[PDB]
Length: 408
Ligand SMILES: [Ca+2]
Ligand SMILES: [Ca+2]
Ligand SMILES: [Ca+2]
Image 1 (spheres, helix red, strand yellow):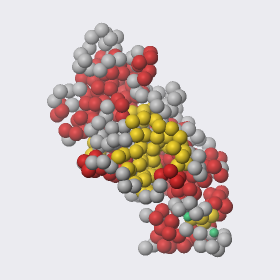
Image 2 (tube, rainbow, N blue to C red):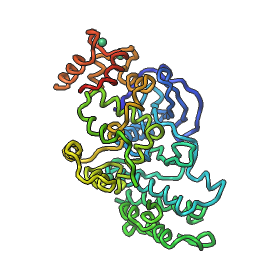
Image 3 (cartoon, rainbow, N blue to C red):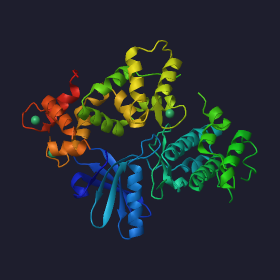
Image 4 (cartoon, helix red, strand yellow):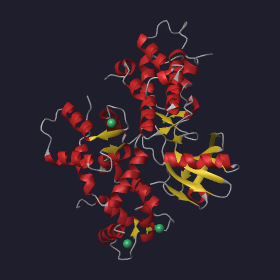
């Protein structure tokens, strides 16, 4: 769902502010002229080929990622001198900012952070991706709120395909050590600030910072370490419409399904952070994806005894999909409620994405790009149901009606 454009960036976005300076170019705050959504825009100067090759390597990696702790990539632009990434806008709050102010984290609060970092590494490694550059500067809190999740915001040195995995593990140990005592390691040495920190924490740090890569613990081992399990131990409460929406998602038309996915991608950390929190609570192996078993066990834990046949059908649909699991954004798309999304300002977001040339109408050529043969069948069915004009295209009024109709 991540398209590349060749037009002028500034035709779609207002550049509202410069946010900072990266190694390969600046980052700006951008505002979509039509939807008024805010993004971070990462500018990468195509000055040298070694760098240019990194830029596209990063783009190909980021297209694969969908995780609560990983920054979203929405689209890209490219001209002669630059490549631009249109990305999720986070806060400017760095991981160690509170240490500058208040000192070292408590172990409970440090564990909350480490669980998120470990989960992201696990997710990446499970995709056969190594980050290779997990320095503290590559993280940002998604918002200024104290409840904010942490996000990895840069994948410039990441590689799709180990000694590399062990380096990611090592990097996480450096961060953990710093969170707990307020200074970096080697500038495992437990001294005046460590006299009060738990033996569980020391043991984990010891496993993460093992000098010989081959004796270093795996990401699975870190996640299952007593320090993580004990300190972050907490019960899950479904929303009132969650299961209804979940079982209904599959029967929606293909355009509405994509629209909900785009909407979910924009609201995940605010309007629907309830659903995000439910996803995370259900994902007990912290893999960033849900198996049918996680959902079943989760429901049983909640109090459901005899699972209704229509929920069993959802479970089987998950088992039998592309992989046997449901991704983070797909779960959000399937659970989000019309009370949240059925608003012109929200629905305009996916409409503007579909309406590539900004015509005000979605054409067949645009749908052909959107739907990745029998794809022509789907487009035909779509237009038969949605094009109440007969003009062969979908305008915003027709789109809003499609989003609001109850009949499958
Ligand atoms: Ca999982
Ligand atoms: Ca158009
Ligand atoms: Ca029409």
